[PDB]
Amino acid sequence: TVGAVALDLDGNLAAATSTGGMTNKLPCTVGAAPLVGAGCYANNASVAVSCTGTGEVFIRALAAYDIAALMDYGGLSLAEACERVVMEKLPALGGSGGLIAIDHEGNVALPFNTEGMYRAWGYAGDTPTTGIYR
Amino acid sequence: TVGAVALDLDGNLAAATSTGGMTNKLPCTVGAAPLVGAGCYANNASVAVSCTGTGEVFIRALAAYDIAALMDYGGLSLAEACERVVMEKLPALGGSGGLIAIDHEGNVALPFNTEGMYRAWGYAGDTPTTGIYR
Amino acid sequence: KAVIAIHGGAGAIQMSLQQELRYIEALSAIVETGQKMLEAGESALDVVTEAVRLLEECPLFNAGIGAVFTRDETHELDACVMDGNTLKAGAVAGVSHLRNPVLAARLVMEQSPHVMMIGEGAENFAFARGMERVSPEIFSTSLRYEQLLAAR
Amino acid sequence: GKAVIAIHGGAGAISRAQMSLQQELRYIEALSAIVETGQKMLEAGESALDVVTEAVRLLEECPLFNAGIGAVFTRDETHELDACVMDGNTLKAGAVAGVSHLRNPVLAARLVMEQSPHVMMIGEGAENFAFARGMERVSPEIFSTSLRYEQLLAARKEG
Ligand SMILES: [Cl-]
Ligand SMILES: [Cl-]
Ligand code: NA
Ligand code: NA
Image 1 (cartoon, helix red, strand yellow):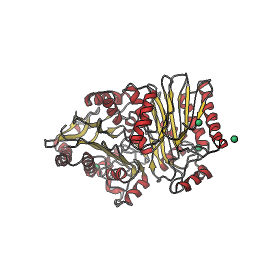
Image 2: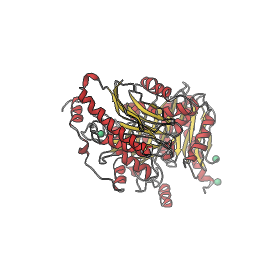
Image 3: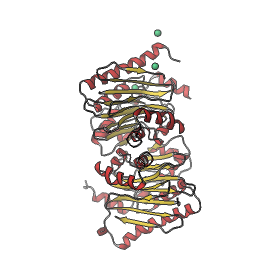
């Protein structure tokens, strides 16, 4: 899996996700990447989210939409909603992975519960930040 | 689309949904019925939901899980959450249809915004209710 | 406080009383089946599985036998089941050679590493685990064919 | 808030012991070029929807990341690709699953969003919809890389 999230100068949010799945997968199987609210979600009222990791668990957890609902309904900060989903709710179901999220105020989060996640972010007009490890 | 939700004597919730799709649909299109959080959702701690209606709208609005999230994080009753999803949020995206829902406390709701919904419900050891029109 | 609810589809529902009574009669029989199972201590999972199996078998309702026609005069069926006790789920999409998609959805929940399978792979997964192959001609009804021509 | 982009190329058991600094820099260089393209587009006033589409098209093209070129192999030594895109303004989405003959599944997902009344298409029908709207048919052998084939052999027994 790969993905991207963005907030533009007009205040609009968007998310996208693309994958080839897991090595040695049976054909005609579908994980989180193409499923709205599992692998991918965006709403101008809350957040844009793109996910990576165990497909069966990100679906059962509705991981991407759960971030949006915790913020919009629950009044959690992006930081608290990402900690709740990635560090507590996914591992409790045996889900390993992470995601990238940007909220309507331009706060950014790149949580993961794995050894690593290939990742990068940057503000318009600023130097980018890159990472691999924790 | 058809569907069923149940609360058993042990407090377990479950949901199931099945369909032939829309008359005259493009083959290879997928609506809400087989997608977790769109056409079908169950959680012992919250609610069981099965949906019927405009597939692309029930997907974009994550209608089945949104019932669970409005109750868990928003403080809405089952009846309040059902009113808000089916009569407000689905029409705002151009969607028509309805859903059946049972909460973990045994409250039951069968909301719809259409001319009719083939439906029935009953407590164990009681006489059932049926309906077609509003 | 055990309880069941069922639906047979929402939309623009013309009909005579005898026509409407066939729908009321089918809804009443299936909801009473589920009520009796719940009273006997059967699980919520087994109740919704059986209720949707019966809605699939009933030609009045758009699932299994009585499925609507696509633009190509074919049938494509989809189903999902979720267990609120384990949070496990199973689903099939775009299947035409399985009589009861909800039973195939349950096999995926119980035996697949994945929530969802599609098309010929979903069918072969179910056949490999003892489920029967059917021709999609078995789903065809005169009423749904007439509804296709009316839509055209 | 300031305009901003984040990207990812997957989570998992990535370890310091596994790579040289030069091998790490190949991943860092790829992630940097893609976020830079995204930052330049945002600064010029381009939409969040067009920015996330272009960023995922680049991640697909990059053979280091498991989407598009560099996809993992299935059990049958094939490739099967899935993608989704969502617009936070209109709440429209598009998605494809189970496609093997489209070079860039995120572009086919964007076509489903913009040029149909549907959110999701699957398999040969998804491909036929895209081909009817001028998208190219490719052979799935285009996605194949030596590194991902060696990962397939390490994860199985030979018959
Ligand atoms: Cl009535
Ligand atoms: Cl009469
Ligand atoms: Na039927
Ligand atoms: Na790639």
